[PDB]
Image (cartoon, rainbow over all chains, first blue to last red; front, side, top):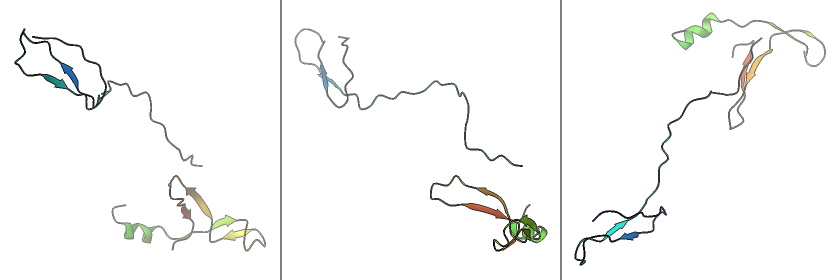
Length: 54
Length: 53
């Protein structure tokens, strides 16, 4: 029943079959569209150009 | 302030010192540069001056 470990490559369909003896089930095709690095970040500073006023 | 038109009535033109008076001598001139601010990417210079146009 369960369990394959597929590699991450985009747009390329990986074929996993891992089901019970005798194949008659649903073949698993899985694609990675994109991976999405979602940040958990700390803001160090803001910087910009500046106007000194005399 | 709260209305741009009203602000400009309030803020009459003034004199400033300018050393260039036709490049002929140093005098109080009606025009002087207060500060030029730029950081635009289309080369635009925002000029602040003594005079009111």
